Image (cartoon, helix red, strand yellow):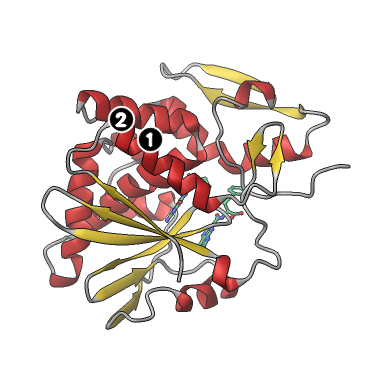
Amino acid sequence: QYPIINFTTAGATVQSYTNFIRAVRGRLTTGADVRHEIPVLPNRVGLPINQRFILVELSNHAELSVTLALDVTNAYVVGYRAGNSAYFFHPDNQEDAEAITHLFTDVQNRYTFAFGGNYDRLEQLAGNLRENIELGNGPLEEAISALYYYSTGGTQLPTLARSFIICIQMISEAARFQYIEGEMRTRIRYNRRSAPDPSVITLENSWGRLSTAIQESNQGAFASPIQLQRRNGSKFSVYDVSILIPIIALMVYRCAPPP
Ligand SMILES: Nc1nc2nc(C(=O)N[C@@H](CCc3ccccc3)C(=O)O)cnc2c(=O)[nH]1
Ligand SMILES: Nc1nc2nc(C(=O)N[C@@H](CCc3ccccc3)C(=O)O)cnc2c(=O)[nH]1
């Protein structure tokens, strides 16, 4: 029913990852909403359930596969399927709880985690912050195996949480931000794993705020500046959508566009 995009970490290259992220973005956005050259994700209000999700099938060199489900309104990873079992994060509201009942309906074992899927909760369970969790093709390869083996008891909860953190950043954050996609491309190009620097972290943390500031802006001009960080941790201010056009690939819907 829902569209499926395939990616493998097995022999992954800059080009194959680029093709993957492009395809994810294409399935997330309809083209109906572009503001200051930046696409906006579908509005959740009145969005039919048959259009609510996309599926990301991740394969690895170990010949294992897992399927992530992403909410098109925000690119949120709501859960995953591995073989005969599916696992969903504790839904944030009743609407999102109803929505996940439409996912992996043929699966033998359905589970909802007692914990939500936001970074703060996942970092708590992992026993590590995003700033200390390595990203790259190797981490993703390993994350796929960890998600696959969870149902059989091979994967400890901190490892599972860490693995979610890897997947979310390398798929959802990369889809949201050309900048983060670029950072992942670099890791893949040189096959060098590394934790995300402050520029990546602050962009992730600011996605909602940046989306709102752009959409509420006066002809692109922010009413209030937004503070981001450089690679070295130094602060720089964003006053305008213009500087964000090469940085942000997708925005969450926050308000109606002005006439
Ligand atoms: N399962 C899952 N968890 C996610 N968690 C976050 C996350 O917690 N992000 C930031 C900013 C707030 C935010 C931004 C976008 C979506 C939700 C929440 C933070 O609070 O540090 C971000 N994205 C996702 C995601 O795509 N899948
Ligand atoms: N399907 C699903 N979606 C979820 N989305 C979020 C979440 O924080 N979503 C926000 C993300 C964008 C945002 C806006 C304003 C400030 C920060 C971040 C949204 O869609 O407005 C949390 N949890 C869930 C969840 O459990 N299931």
**Most distant residue in the right direction:** 259
Q: Nearer the viewer, residue 91 or 84?
A: 84
Identify the disc placed on residue 18. 1
Q: Nearer the viewer, residue 58 or 129?
A: 58
User: Residue 97: image x %, image y %?
Assistant: 51, 74
Q: Residues within 10 Å of mark 1 (few under 14, many from 20)?
A: some
Q: Nearer the viewer, residue 25 or 143?
A: 25
Location of residue 200 with respect to 111 vertically, above or below: above
- Contact between marks 2 and 1 (CB within 8 A): the answer is yes
Q: Report the residue at 28% width, 54% height from top.
A: 58
Q: Report the residue at 70% width, 46% height from top.
A: 33
**Cα distance between the residues tagged 2 and 1:** 6 Å
Q: Name the residue type under label 2.
A: Val
Location of residue 115 with respect to 60 vertically, above or below: below
Does the residue tagged 1 have its C-beta within 8 Å of any atom of ligand 1?
Answer: no
Does the residue tagged 2 have its C-beta within 8 Å of any atom of ligand 1?
Answer: no
Q: Is residue 140 visible?
A: yes
Q: Circle 2 is placed at which residue position?
A: 14
User: Residue 20: image x %, image y %?
Assistant: 37, 43
Local secondary structure at mark 1: helix
Q: Residues within 10 Å of mark 2 (few under 14, many from 20)?
A: some
Q: Report the residue at 54% width, 27% height from top.
A: 247
In the displayed structure image, the side of residue 50 where residue 47 appears, left or right: right
User: Residue 60: image x %, image y %?
Assistant: 18, 50
